[PDB]
Image (tube, rainbow, N blue to C red):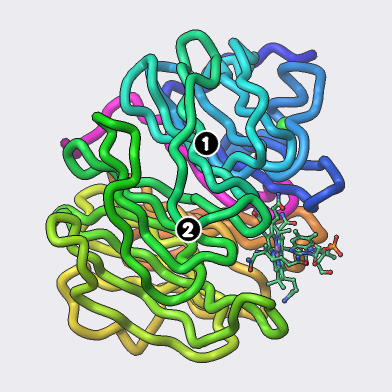
Amino acid sequence: MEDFSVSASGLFITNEGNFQYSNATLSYYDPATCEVENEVFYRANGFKLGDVAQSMVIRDGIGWIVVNNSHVIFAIDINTFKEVGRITGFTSPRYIHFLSDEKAYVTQIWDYRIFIINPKTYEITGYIECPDMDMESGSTEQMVQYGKYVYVNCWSYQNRILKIDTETDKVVDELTIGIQPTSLVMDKYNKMWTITDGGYEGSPYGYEAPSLYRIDAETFTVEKQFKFKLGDWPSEVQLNGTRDTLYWINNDIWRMPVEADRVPVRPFLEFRDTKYYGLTVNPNNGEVYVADAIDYQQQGIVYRYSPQGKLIDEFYVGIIPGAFCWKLEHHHHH
Ligand code: CNC
Ligand SMILES: [Cl-]
């Protein structure tokens, strides 16, 4: 076991590792020193994260790491990386969304329910049943808040956004769109963005040209749709800190102002026959980080770009780096 006491400002990278090989890891990058630290959860705690580290949220000095195929969320000190607690019993957890210190939602694959937890006591307290959904093909994924409502995309073998009333913990509406919306963000106009992966060739569920959608939160209606090419396998809508510039992965890294009527001809970062897989925008300074899985086998590489697309830095992370979590001392945005 190793003692860490890292920067007040930094960047976590979760590494999924290889599904069913239990080689998921956590990386910590200091943008001021341009130094990366790899395998920091193992190094700090003396045991493995597990299988498919999916996502991470930082709240009140604690990092909540979702380990999808280990049925657990780890709570860590964001400075020492030491575990302060864990929640077990998740079917196959995906994303955590906090409503309070005592209430959060945890989405699942292979379950038709969203888990309700108490992060304070580290307990599962209840379940939200998704309509028209079973265990065999169930999927809830990313979440955004809109007043008293949480919106959630249904990804694997699903084609819906659900609306949850957080005051009753019930799904109160749904919207059917293209198959397998991957990810969900809310822009500063309270308009949601989601991008579909289009399924895959030979899928028992579907295989189609994928789309990027803008969905008004108030009317819960599609306002814009940008359809791509059959065989495209897009992912990971991401916003800048002012929530007026959208990024996503579709071979290339794409950038579009949220009020645009057309996807720009030119991508932010050109495809280079690798596997762009993870994406984030520094919420304070607009710097763009691209996690490249390369070939899903070797150590991944993160590329750090200026908001104008000029390379700043590049560093190795773990295998299949999938997600980022910002550790910021101050947020410039409200
Ligand atoms: C590439 C890939 C990946 N996939 Co697929 C995705 N997205 N996937 C695919 C594709 C594989 C073929 C291709 N076009 O390249 C593709 C699009 C067909 C696919 C399909 C699926 N995938 C699916 C899921 C959910 C997953 N996939 C990942 C394994 C997920 C991977 C991410 C990860 N962290 O592992 C992943 C990004 C990289 C796998 C890889 O090539 N590794 C390198 C390779 C050398 O190692 P490998 O051990 O031989 O990998 C093989 C397996 O991973 C297998 N496989 C891939 N996905 C699954 C899912 C399941 C349930 C099973 C049993 C096997 C697989 O295919 C690979 C090629 O043989 C996953 C961990 C991503 C995630 N972070 O959630 C996740 C499984 C989570 C879980 N707890 O079950 C689908 C259910 C998604 C969907 N509804 O479209 C579906 C299931 C197919 C099935 N039942 O076999
Ligand atoms: Cl680790």
Disc marking residue 102: none
Q: Residue at x 79, y 52 (%)?
A: 18
Question: 333 above or below 274?
Answer: above
Question: Can you identify the residue that label 2 sits on?
Answer: 132
Cα distance between the residues tagged 2 and 1: 29 Å
Residue 292: % across, % down: 63, 62
Mark 2: which amino acid?
A: Asp
Query: Toward the viewer: 263 or 292?
Result: 263
Magenta-drawn stretch contains 164: no
Report whether 298 appears left or right of 148: right
Q: Residue at x 81, y 58 (%)?
A: 298
Mark 1: which amino acid?
A: Met
Question: 27 above or below 285?
Answer: above
Q: Which residues are magenta?
A: 314-334
Mark 1 lies within 8 Å of ligand 2 (Cβ measured): no
Q: Residue at x 64, y 15 (%)?
A: 83
